[PDB]
Picture 1: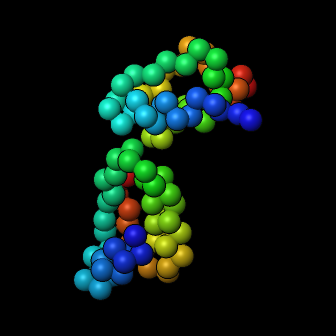
Picture 2 (picture 1 turned 45 degrees about the vertical axis):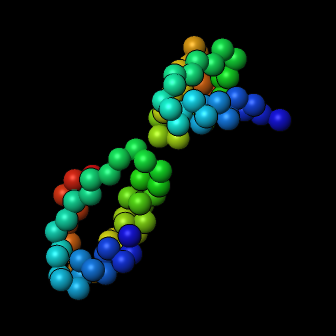
Length: 49
Length: 49
């Protein structure tokens, strides 16, 4: 998830959404992203989960 | 110990064979994500609230 964020940051794609399924680790994925996205000063947008 | 009927929910679950517990009031089976074939006769301790 971190690498996905780094990739997005590299291309400076600030605005994104997450499509997930009930498959394992889905809830945390959101949590890990919530921390990683949240900590940064930048105003990127999570649109939908 | 507790939650003796953990394996079956997984085992049937691979083939999506529905499982119905009689005596498992355990709450951990309520999440569809981990046990997706689980069928419960009665509500968990959480629902007791």
